[PDB]
Length: 53
Length: 496
DNA sequence: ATTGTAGCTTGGATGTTGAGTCA
DNA sequence: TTGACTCAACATCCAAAGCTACAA
Image (cartoon, rainbow over all chains, first blue to last red; front, top):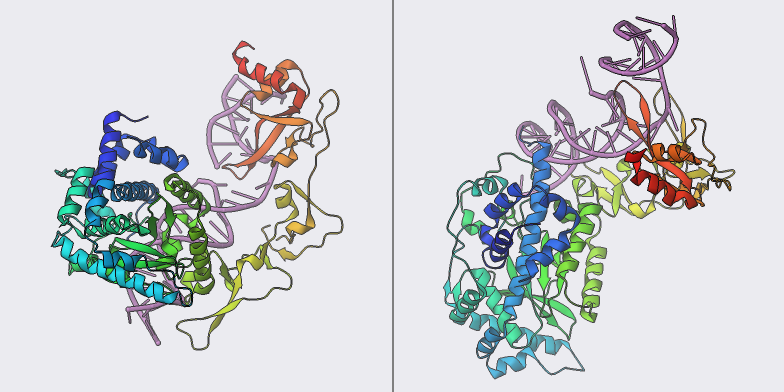
């Protein structure tokens, strides 16, 4: 249940700028407490999210 | 001391997972980019005809090895001309994709930084011009080999932060930091050799070698310094056909004893989680090559054998030290040790090593009832153990136990209940065949309101202060034909 | 008031972690 | 440069259906 802007940033970093992962994930995981439980139970959903567009 | 809180422990485990997933997705996407047609038509022109023929030698019946030979020579010549192609190599701006410390990750959020974006087109342009860090270099190389229609994998040694490192201060030695970090690569290449039926390891940029890994690999980092930024635990292979295979086994000499400790897979949950990620990234059907590689991994597993040190046998997936057999375990009849351990530090001191497949777990009668099992007629106990005010508890094996079948409910749906007026239901087995368990805070109030025949369900035991255990009545066992009636009452509880 | 309830101060055995010492 | 010790501070697993005093 994330925004368009964050999923866009995440895909752009993952695809071409993964050296910048550390601070982005710091921000996102600090702003999305729910993400923890999502990753733990449904990692494939997250993967496919990133794999779209 | 120097150990952080448990909250930090869990935060590090979660961040480790998240980071790993992101890295693996990065490898997938980069492997897509590598498949770009626009790029391959350009890189194809870098490989002379002679070399193409060497990369696709004629099948040699009498002695397939000679063909392997010609293949390897082509790969070598490809490596040579790749040096000619690239020319400019850039340094990694900040540790590239080598492992970062927790302190570094903590402070990275502290200070923001401008990041020059790399789009697919930028990647293609950089690879064609021959400009970039060693990672982009090797990636281009894999793209070239693929342009020449050879089955070349991109290999990524994923370096998430180490969730086993529980230190607060995680400082690193600055002396030769970069040189030690770049001593071994993060990305390299694997090429399938159809003649010998093995993956050949190729690092054309960093170590500039080709090897046919048997037991030892030149690419696994060695030395405490080097393993502080390069902890080999997730070596991932991406192929032409968008496959994704965990290939650590090839490059880790001690997968089962050492590496396992440092992997999220060390427990059942992480095992399933990682299998889910792989599957999510594995976009192809199984091939015969997979079968060959699995046989290779199986032989590598067979020949890793018992580890040389006591620590490496703590929580080993296959072996247990005699002294680590729990008080509630026995050696399966007729079995013995499967090996020994020379104890480093004591002359002629030796420990007995058992295969875990040969250790049986025993439980007492009560414990079995807690697993919905009673003892068979004339079962004899296998072990006797103390407890507290002491007490001699007998232990039995699974084979001495039987599945408990509770009596059926009557026609009217009346359940037969224990001395406290409750039914104990610790296992699905323990629900009567013609009954169902309804778990709900108000399932009791509901069944009482309908005046129907039920039985409160004791599903577990709450341990609480004072000194006293308490039963957890989480719901109701009713006959099956009354389920929806109960479910209706439950749904309308506000109206009672 | 002869019942309803707040309060009693999970624990005890066993494993994990990093630091340090030794051979 | 190796690993087997020990130390101490937590963490984690696992048992498995109360008891007293006192206010109302």
